[PDB]
Each structure stands twice: as structure tokens, then as C-alpha cells.
Amino acid sequence: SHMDEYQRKIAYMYDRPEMAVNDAQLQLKVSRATTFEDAYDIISKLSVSDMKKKLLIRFRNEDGLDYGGVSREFFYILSHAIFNPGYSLFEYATDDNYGLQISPLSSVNPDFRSYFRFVGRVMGLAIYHRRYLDVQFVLPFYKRILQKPLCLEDVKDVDEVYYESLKWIKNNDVDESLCLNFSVEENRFGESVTVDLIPNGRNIAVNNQNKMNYLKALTEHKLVTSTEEQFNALKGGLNELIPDSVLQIFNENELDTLLNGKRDIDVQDWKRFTDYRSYTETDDIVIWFWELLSEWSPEKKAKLLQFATGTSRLPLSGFKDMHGSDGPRKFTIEKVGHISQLPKAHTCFNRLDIPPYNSKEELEQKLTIAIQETAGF
Amino acid sequence: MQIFVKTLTGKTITLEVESSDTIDNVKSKIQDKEGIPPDQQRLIFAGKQLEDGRTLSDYNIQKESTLHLVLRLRG
Amino acid sequence: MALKRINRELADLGKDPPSSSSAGPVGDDLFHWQATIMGPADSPYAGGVFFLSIHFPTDYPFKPPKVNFTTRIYHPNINSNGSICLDILRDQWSPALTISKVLLSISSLLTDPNPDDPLVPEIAHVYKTDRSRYELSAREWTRKYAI
Image 1 (cartoon, rainbow over the protein chains, first blue to last red):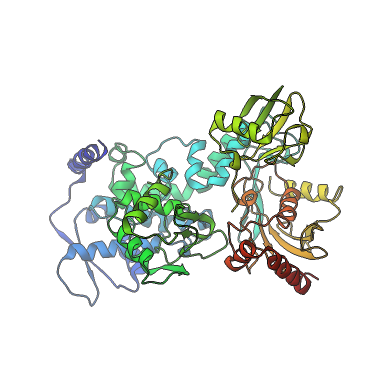
Image 2: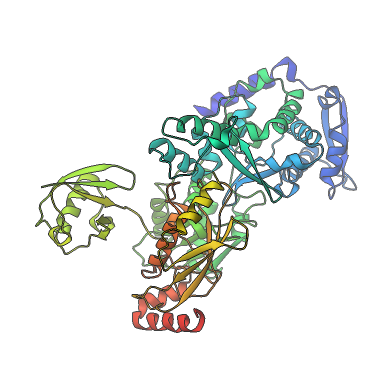
């Protein structure tokens, strides 16, 4: 069983003598509006001995009990602040598939090492004090944290179309018509520059006897070499608190569970940020739909979300900042089709066509049948 | 005669058909071999898409003919 | 891989153009192209000219370009903004595909509209209800906008 083994691993990890908290208290005061600034001002100067004590967090001018909830809210705010793409530290892998990864442009700052060491300290503090962030990275990130080799299949999580093109090159032979060579053009702040995968790489065409080396170099440069210094600083900050010999007992999924907790999809946000065509908020095929979504397991909700939108990952701010093929396209429900036909999905517009059924049982049966081939989480 | 149909995934399927065989008959053969319903099958030979109600001879399909199957939707 | 390929595509288009659809860089910016499409003569858009904007991502040819319309059209699969949901440009893309195949696919789509993907539900409903009225409206829009 996965759950029992993971619980055994967690107990063994937190039972280690090198991951035990002290008894003294460390008061940490941050203003709610300026959470990021105060967090970076305090955390990035604490000593390693200080960071191993009990963490007590008190927002300014907000006195109250149940410090556990306060600390959880603080970590939620900090994780939604530092990992926000607008801050030019991390970025989505693709606009229509929201997966966080280190942004190559982050090197533009004069000193990105301090900020990434702060991010590493934040993640180590979250893991060390049994507090959960709420971001969703890509699997290559977790595999890099644990120091596992990265292969071609790992590009599937980052970008689907890129992985499909690479697999096409791997399968079919490559002629000289395709003007492909050992060089990648990167466009930073408007200026486009050429990076050589291998020395003198811009003058070497990829024949049928080189495409394997080309794929290997492309995957390594896309997943690793483009983010060397930044991720090195981040992992140094992370390993400052958590010794590597502790992180290397998990895998790319147990570490995700340890960091972000058991992932779940909110339903209230989904309802608040959806729109209807030819449907009203008080129609039967809407109230029944929302009741079904209320009384459903997270795996099936994720399967439905992947069936409708196209991916099971959500933006960093919920369904509000949802994107489609063209641009911002919020989840849409439409009345289309005959009674007998199953509900249909248009993924490039996050649109779900639910015909006008007659009863809740029929709606549940049709909707559960229509999403069987879709796998989520 | 024998014909070969290459799918969009590169899979090659050999069919023992005849010039007088209808498009529906070949689509039924493809359905039997792969489970693809005849209405969902899109067969193209020499740039011309095969359509139901006609025969292979209507498309000048000959010995060892090569067809392209595109099992795709629209949208 | 993202500039030599574009130069090769432009050179190929400059050698044997389809004589109907044209494409070229806007001034000097190889990642932003303008395309002109002639209306097919077998569809109610006959005699009309359409303009397209093509953006080549830096991951070209591994990632497909982004194409948008500029002139309105009474088409089920072309929204008001002109965004096109096409399988070749998002799903069935392989590095072997050039930019002339996208233009050929679009010029073919301008003859066989799909109502089952109603990017404008009113137009697709008109198509599914009254074919004659649908084609009349398409011709009226083409006369109003295309030239």
C-alpha cells in the first residue's frame, strides 16, 4: 500500500535525531500586506540554530489564538507570493498547462542567489515544521532535488508538444530538409542569442547518426543546464536544514506529498468562477452537477477537470486566472446535444456540454461513463 | 488483391480486398481488425478521401495499393 | 534551429509559391509574419481576400506557430478575435510540417467548416438549421469585409 509505506517513511524521517526541534520559541512578526518583504528580511538572516527552534508566527495588529492556523495561513501566503510568476522567480511551463519551474530569465537580477537561497530556506522550513505549501511543481524539479538522472520521458510533464516532437525525431529518420543543428536560440528581454549544445555546434547538422546525441543534449539543456546556478543556490538553502541523506529516502511523488500535502481540488472556487451558456444558476442540470461535485472523491474530480479543461493542474490563484488556447477562458458549461448523448468537452476553451437530462441518477451515470478513459492524478 | 493501410501512428495493416469491394466493405474489414467504426474511418488514396457508398475501383485502387488512415476528430 | 529553419521556409516559399497564398516577414522581424489567403472558388467566400498573422515561437520547429485572422468571417470555427482551433497547429504537429502546409490546411478549412466545434455557436446553429441561409450570410459577410 502507498499510504502506509509513506506514513512509515514520514515517521522514520521525523524520528531522526538530526531533525528534532528545540524547546525555545522564535517569535516571527510579519505584516499581512508586505508578507514577502518581511519574510525575506527575517528568514534570510536567521542562523541555522535559530531556524531549528519552535516557530511562532504572529501577524502584526492581528492578535489571536490557535497559532497553528496563523502559521498555516502565513505559509500559504508566502508560498503563493514567492512562487508567483509575476515576481520573476518561477514561471509556468506552458500557459495552458500550469506547471511551475525555475525561470531562466531570473538570472537578470544582479543577485538571484540570495533570493533562491531564501526560497530554499522557506521550503526547508516548511518541510521541517510539518507545514504545507500549496504550489505544484513539475516532476523534473522533484527528481532534481533528489538527484536522479533525467531522461526524455521527463519532458512529458514539462511540455507535451515538445515531448511529442522529440519523440517524433527519435522514431522517424531526419533528412537534411529540416534545418536542425546543435544550437538553441533563446530570446531574453527581446534579444535573441545562440547557445551551442556542443562546441562548434551551430555548424553541425543532425544526421540520422546524431539525432540521439541531439535529443540527449536538448533534454539536458532544457531541464538542467539552463538553471545551474539558481538551482544550486536553491538546493544549498534547502540542504542547510534538511540533510540530503534524509531527502533521498523518498521519490518524486512522496516528496510532492510531503511538501504540498494531499492535493485536492476546491469546489467552491470552481462554482464561483464558472460561467454558463444557455444555462442559469438555478437550473436543474446545474444544481445537480454541483451537488455531484460536492459529494465526490478528489481523484474523480481531477479526472473530470482533465476531461473538460485538458489538464489536471490549476493556476496558482485557482480558477480565476484560468487560460485556454487563445487567452483567459474560464470554465464554461453549455446546453448542447440530445438526451442520449454523453456530455462532451472542448478542451481548448475549457467548455463542457451537458445535455438537458431528467434526473440526478442519469446525470451521474452519464458523467461517470464519459470520463472513464481520462486518468488524473 | 492485397492493400496496405498506414495509420496516422505509422501502423501498417494488410487487407485482402478486391477492386469491386465497396468502401463500406473495406471499412468493415478495418473495423473488424481494429475496432474503428466505419463512420470514424478516414481513408485517403492518391490525395482523394474514400467515401461510403462507392467501391475501390471508383478510386482506381489497384494491386498493392497504399492508403492513409486518419482517425481524427474536428475541433 | 529556430532561425535557419525560418530562413529556409521563406526561401522555399520564394521559389515555388502556391500562387494563391502568400507569406512574408513584416519589415525585418523573422518571428512575425503576415499571410494573405485567397478565398476558395468552391465556397461562398469566393472572390475574397483574408489576412493572417503568424507568430513563430522560439522553440520552432518543436512547437507550432500561432496564427490569427485579421478580417472577420461568418465561419463556425473562427471567433470574433480570429483565433483558430486547428489540430495541426496544436495537436498533430511534427517538425516535418512547414508553414505552407498550415496555409493549405486553412485554405481547405475555408471550404469545409465544422459546426460540431461551434467557436461561434450562432453561426454553427444557422449552419445546422438552414444551409441556404447559412451560405447567404457567409456571402454577405464576405462581401462586407473581405475586400
